């Protein structure tokens, strides 16, 4: 049976500094185990794990962010999606994901970097839901006066419990590689653009994310 | 640091203090020690 | 004095991910060398040291760009300049103490329109520079007043100052007099934030005497 949902995190510095603090400390402890190669190796492994955590946070929050305040802009949705797709294209390969893009050059008002971040987080989740093969569908249309972007995957899907918790800060099913912060920023960005989001999913079958945005002239 | 043994965790704590590692790093270790209900070893 | 130089009211840096990922990648790479096979103690020590220096770099970029940034997109608000300044001073008090810098603040609760995190980031970058210009003592003065319909935020130090050529280059991406610990990205950010707030900046500086940064912002009513 399919289900559908209709729609505190730490500051960015705290979120990134936490793992970097841990990595720095364990790196410095390596030389404090001069007789135990296994303890040195464990320290190094933890440090690397924490550095990978930092990298995951950067991916979720800062993939496109530039060191300058953004200004709201008329965004060509087709072009923005294509660039995000180009970035995730190597990730779709290796995991055998077929990207099918039916797009239209409609315009919405937003901030380019944040909008790209929002799109990346949704699409990356879709690819990660299909670890050993699948199909990624990106579709642009007008739905009752508004720009509809829907992102469908044939992946692992979500139960009702998981789906209702989707976007809750730190909720993840991906273990150490998960942050549970990617969808949270998707929601925040969509809200700021005066949009809405629907997520339909069924376990083992897949997930469809529907983004609704006001049409710009 | 959830996979460190109790033994290695405590060992790391005292070694961090000797080197004067970051107070923030020492606090992370202490919090892990507290989580494991092992503060009586500190 | 006669060496006084001024920058009157009114290119190209890496994206934030690129700037942080460069040192992070290097740090991971060096620790990976230690992890993947047993190395001799001299190489482990060296690789760990380089990794830590690269983590120092990441932390400097985080400081310049992301000290206050929250994952939620910001909305402009009515900002109490006294409260915001006090928050920034609180954060920098340990650093000032470590350089024997005393902080003198004369503040008033005047209001400006802006985005809180960015405004705080802007103030921190200027005050951190002020403290860094005074490595062996001095006074950080922070003054808030009204000047002709504008809020004036004045940040003065008694530090090393700048030549004509250095003040001209201040805010140029990657320009720094601080060598290995410098980023040259702090002021770049300050100018872009103040600009977005419809403000202006005036700087007076004199070698061996110090620097005064004046930020002017529209008064919110
Ligand atoms: N397309 C999807 N298919 C299946 N599960 C998903 C999908 N998108 C999100 N989820 C679930 O929601 C959780 C939170 O997502 P997110 O906030 O991006 O964090 P992360 O991806 O780091 O786990 C994921 O761990 C996953 O269980
Ligand atoms: N208060 C100050 N006193 C003296 N020099 C300053 C001051 N503020 C900025 N500068 C000069 O401008 C340069 C660039 O500043 P900034 O962009 O913050 O980079 P960083 O502080 O990383 O060097 C500094 O390296 C310094 O030479
Ligand atoms: Mg995710
Ligand atoms: Mg600086």
Image: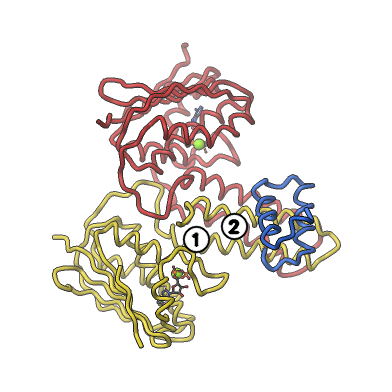
Chain colours: A yellow, B blue, C red
The C terminus of chain C: image quadrant: top left
A211 displayed left or right of A174: left
Disc ID at residue A177: none
A98 displayed left or right of C32: left
Q: Name the quadrant containing residue A37.
A: bottom right
Residue under pointer 1: A57
Q: Which image quarter has ligand 3? A: bottom left
Q: Name the quadrant containing residue C179.
A: top right
Relative vertical location of residue C128 with respect to residue A46 in this rendering, above or below: above
Give how far across and how far down residue A112 sits, in percent.
31, 57
Give how far across and how far down residue A60 sits, in percent.
45, 62
Q: Name the quadrant containing residue C136.
A: top right
Disc ID at residue A19: 2
Q: Which of marks 2 and 1 is nearer the N terminus?
A: 2
Disc 2: residue Cβ within 8 A of ligand 1's nearest atom:
no
- Circle 2/circle 1 CB separation < 8 Å: yes
């Amino acid at each position: 049976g399919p289900h559908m949902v209709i729609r505190l995190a730490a500051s960015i510095s705290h979120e990134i500094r936490n793992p970097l603090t841990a990595a720095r400390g364990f790196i410095q402890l390596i030389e404090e185990q001069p007789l135990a190669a296994d303890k040195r190796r464990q320290y190094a492994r933890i440090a690397i794990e924490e550095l990978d955590r930092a990298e995951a946070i950067i991916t979720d929050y800062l993939t496109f962010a530039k060191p300058a305040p953004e200004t709201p802009e008329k965004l060509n949705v087709k072009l923005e999606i294509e660039r995000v797709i180009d970035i995730l294209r190597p990730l779709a390969n290796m995991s055998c994901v077929d990207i099918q893009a039916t797009l239209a050059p409609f315009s919405v008002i937003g901030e380019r970097e944040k909008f790209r971040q929002c799109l990346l987080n949704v699409m990356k989740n879709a690819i990660e839901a299909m670890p050993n093969g699948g199909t990624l569908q990106v579709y642009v249309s007008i739905d009752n006066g508004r720009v509809l972007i829907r992102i469908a995957d044939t992946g692992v899907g979500m139960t009702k419990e998981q789906l209702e918790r989707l976007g809750e800060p730190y909720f993840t099913t991906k273990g150490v590689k998960g942050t549970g912060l990617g969808m949270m920023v998707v929601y925040r960005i969509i809200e700021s653009m005066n949009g809405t989001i629907r997520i339909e999913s069924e376990i083992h079958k897949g997930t469809t994310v529907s983004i609704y945005l006001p049409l710009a002239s | 640091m959830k996979h460190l043994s109790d033994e290695l965790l405590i060992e790391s704590y005292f070694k961090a203090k000797e080197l004067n590692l970051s107070p923030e790093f020492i606090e992370l270790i202490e919090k892990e020690i507290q989580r494991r209900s092992l503060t009586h070893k500190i």
